[PDB]
Image (spheres, rainbow, N blue to C red):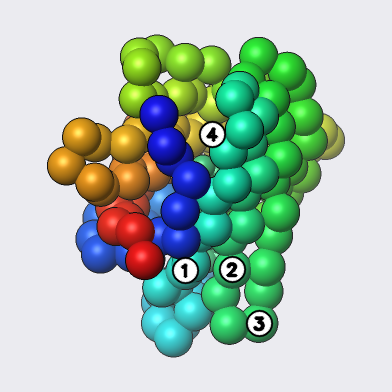
């Protein structure tokens, strides 16, 4: 349906846990989830094609994909990867990520629109699941 919107975050869960598995050391994680961990997500959708903009106060990243087509992006912690999004339901999609170079935790993310107006991102590294919940602006 209409994933498109200007999304403001309302709930974070396990974001520091995620960062830990990803290997960001302690002081870095703590300091990280501080004044720059309340992110804005902008979504413009046209069919199976997605344009996404995620930004803090000094950083912004653009993610562009079509469902079913490989692309390149970033892991949550900054490492470049190849990604592929699939649908798992009418309102939910799943992305498997494979690192470009190196090794590290197995990462993935999902994007779901609840019928109640919540946009729900999850990000997974090995067995830790960070859940972010947004509502529109
Ligand atoms: C469909 C929505 C997607 C793919 C959203 C992805 C969001 C991120 C990869 C967020 C990354 C973040 C940073 C790069 C630093 C600030 C903390 C986060 C989680 C907002």
Sequence-first disc among 1 and 3: 1
Residue at image mark 1: 39
Q: Give the answer, above or below, for where 134 lies relative to 88.
A: below
Residue at image mark 3: 58
Residue at image mark 2: 55
What separation in Å lies between label 4 and label 3 (alpha carbons)?
25 Å
Residue mark closest to the camera, 4 vs 3: 3
Q: Residue at x 45, y 24 (%)?
A: 93
- Label 3 neighbourhood size at 10 Å, few (<14), some (14-19), many (20+)? few
Residue 92 at x, y = what percent? 38, 25
Q: Residue at x 66, y 29 (%)?
A: 49
- Label 1 neighbourhood size at 10 Å, few (<14), some (14-19), many (20+)? some
Q: Give the answer, above or below, for where 3 lies relative to 28.
A: above
Q: Residue at x 66, y 44 (%)?
A: 51
Mark 3 and mark 2 residues within 8 Å of each other at the beta carbon: no
Q: Secondary structure at mark 4?
A: strand
């Amino acid at each position: 349906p209409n994933f498109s919107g200007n999304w403001k975050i309302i709930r974070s869960e396990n974001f520091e846990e995620l960062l830990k598995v990803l290997g960001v050391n302690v002081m870095l994680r703590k300091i990280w989830v501080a004044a720059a961990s309340k992110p804005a997500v902008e979504i413009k959708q046209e069919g199976d094609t997605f344009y996404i903009k995620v930004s803090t106060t000094v950083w912004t990243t653009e993610i562009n994909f079509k469902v079913g087509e490989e692309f390149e992006e970033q892991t949550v912690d900054g490492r470049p990867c190849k990604s592929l999004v699939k649908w798992e339901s009418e309102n939910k999609m799943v992305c498997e990520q494979k690192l470009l170079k190196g090794e590290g935790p197995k990462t993935s993310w999902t994007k779901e629109l609840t019928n109640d107006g919540e946009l729900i991102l999850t990000m997974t590294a090995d067995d830790v699941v960070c859940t972010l919940v947004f509502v529109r602006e």
